[PDB]
Length: 126
Image 1: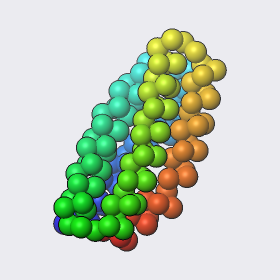
Image 2: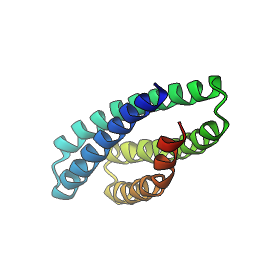
Image 3: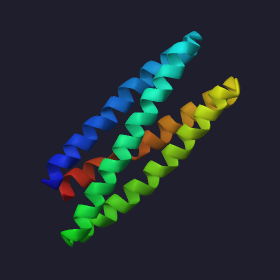
Image 4: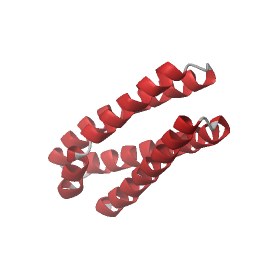
């Protein structure tokens, strides 16, 4: 069901959460080769999560589930904020700008932490 597709998408997000916190440790420790690999792994996870979310939203639309569609539109918008912050973090790593990288990492944690009370609302709405 759309609900099980959501629990599958939620797990992928929690995989990115895990890798992100591991990546933050490697950055703090100066293990740039680890960071590079973790950033690639995060890109693939965010691309997978985004595709799953879009399928879930499209299903809710086709099912006429207006409340789920509303919540998924809000959640997908915030998801794209994170994607932009993430992509800015990746560019800062390429450029050797640790100041920006730190900044973007905190910003991404905050945008992520905020968009969680909604993530639980969507699980109940589908």
